[PDB]
Amino acid sequence: VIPWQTFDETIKELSRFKQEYSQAASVLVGDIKTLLMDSQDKYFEATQTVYEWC
Amino acid sequence: GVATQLLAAYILLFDEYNEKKASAQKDILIKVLDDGITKLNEAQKSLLVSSQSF
């Protein structure tokens, strides 16, 4: 009359969805942030070198 | 610190044209500038790598 086992297992699958997706997402987001900072640094160096020549 | 004193010595000793220390002076200037440019470029590249490290 209270299928609490099935209820809890449902909640388990539901939570496990969001666990997996947070896990997959945040790593790649951090990779993006790294590449953004790297491109920034390359840009700074290139512009600096040009300006110093000019 | 060395550069600013060498250049002041250049201005002071060559207000006029002494022909005797003329040839040595060019050697001194070439030596100090070829040293300092290399120093500065290596320092900048090291700082760039240090910036990229984060």
Image (cartoon, coloured by chain):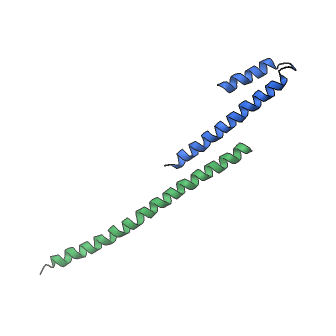
Chain colours: A green, B blue
Rendered residue at 16%/76% (across/down): A4
Looking at the rendering, in which quadrant would you find the C terminus of chain A?
Answer: top right
Q: Is residue A30 shown above or below B4?
A: below
Q: Quadrant of the N terminus of chain A?
A: bottom left
Residue in the foreground of this view, choosing between A33 and B23:
B23
Which quarter of the figure has residue A29?
bottom left
**At 83% across and 26% down in the image, what residue appears?**
B23
Which residue sits at x=58%, y=45%? B48
Residue A5 percent coordinates (x, y): 16, 76
- Asked whether A16 or B30 is in front, the reply is B30
Q: Residue furthest left?
A: A1
**Residue B45 sits in which quadrant?**
top right
Is A25 positioned to the left or the right of B40 in the image?
left
Q: Dividing the picture into quarters, in which one does residue B24 lie?
A: top right
Q: Residue furthest bottom?
A: A1
Is residue A24 left or right of A49 when viewed as pictured?
left
In the image, A50: left or right of A9?
A: right
In the image, residue A37 sits, relative to residue A3, either above or below, namely above
Which residue shows up at 64% across the image and 36% down it?
Answer: B39
Q: Is residue B28 above or below residue A49?
A: above
Count the labels in the image. Answer: 0
Q: Position of residue B19 (x, y in %)?
A: 88, 20
Residue A6 position (above or below residue B5) = below
Where does the image place residue B54, in percent across and percent down from the top left? 48, 49
Residue A19 screen position, x and y as percent:
32, 67
Side (left or right) of A6 relative to A33: left
